Image (cartoon, rainbow over all chains, first blue to last red; front, side, top):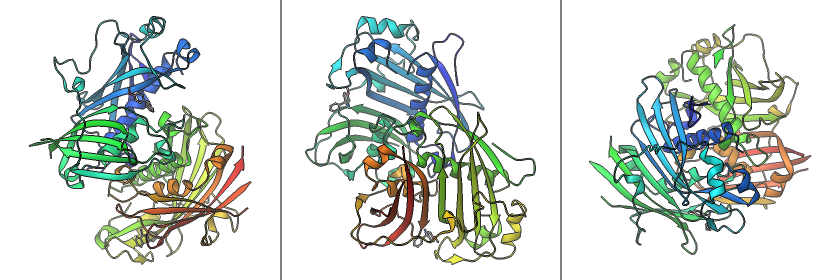
Length: 265
Length: 264
Ligand SMILES: COc1ccc([C@H](N)c2ccccc2)cc1
Ligand SMILES: COc1ccc([C@H](N)c2ccccc2)cc1
């Protein structure tokens, strides 16, 4: 992978692996989510980071995802090359936004796109912080000044409020626990694991007869290594819509809320 | 990746990803197991397999792993390039063997090696079958004629019998269930998930202070999508462990294995 000529975005090609595909021999949305995470990490490395700034490392501050929104038109098949372009942007004092564009390497056609919202958080106290002006200047040199949105639209599906699923849920998957493969290099549960846990409560018939078009996921609380999660889903709706909720198996503490959109095959 | 000049083995380079590494910023043994599986698939595709041959498809026959043995000396760090070479061999009518050699792309040094034993099984009846003529001839053209072993040592760790763990186990991780990410393209639980489940019962103190050197795993029964597994471990001893995976309910054995860990 490499930064584009202007140094304001990063591109990388990925060959889809045998273990990265589902029943239709195309990449799973969890594989896509891993690739977006990987290309975002390589963008930070290529711009002199390791993705906290000098001031953030000093103040015990980290970036935490608040929302992830993925829209897929064509899932890359096993053996195909997918090119992903990613860039960052400052959204005032609220936080930062990272956008992604997925393309077919043989045709050059846009096969997918993603957007994510990141807020600052003190590593230790877990308290959210607004972006300090000094921190803003430290990464404005790596972001385009003019707005560049993967989801430009006037009232797009990436910026819409998600309601809370009410009991009883239509479907559920109970007793979900992360294993060591679900942890990242800092022993935190990987953001991609939450996507997989959300999709666990969608019935296998819907997964076998439909394809995932859109997924919007809000991160509320972090699942610990020793926590147990319940995944709940209710059909809200040729297309199918679902309302999702991840919560602690015990006290019902909310960890995630989301929505999925599926098109009939 | 590409076949070597003689067409009797396959090589592929892999750049280690951020999500593929553990706490020491080096690849997990599950990441290595996935890469060996990936390089074995690309070897089959490059030699004309769209690896169930043409005769096996007519007979509803598939290759199933009976044993996987991995020995790692140096785990590739995040961002490093690891080159893996893989080849196949016939072992008479018992089945086939696939070996792997892992190398550092910058130094050319051997950082790991693996071996696996595969037996034939009827897809439908689940009955094991000895390898017959026509089938042997079909893939003998892709295997070296002279013996080429990743573990040449006469009577080595990869060809040793594994005992059954007796109750009570020293450590345990119960209620393990596979999710859709644990399934392969044919909806079966992939062989790498079993490695992860075995390691779940090793205490976090051993994982934080030791490095995994050897893992030998025997596959006895397949875990279904709706099955629940219990992972059991006992220290037999460097540190040595005896492992057992079994159905949470009736205690049906699905796997047995051994791990060897070196102090950091
Ligand atoms: C804005 O969204 C988030 C904010 C903070 C968290 C954080 N991991 C957490 C852990 C434990 C308890 C509460 C918060 C996660 C998401
Ligand atoms: C010699 O090693 C094996 C033999 C057979 C199996 C197979 N998956 C299985 C599934 C269900 C019931 C019995 C066998 C796996 C390994």
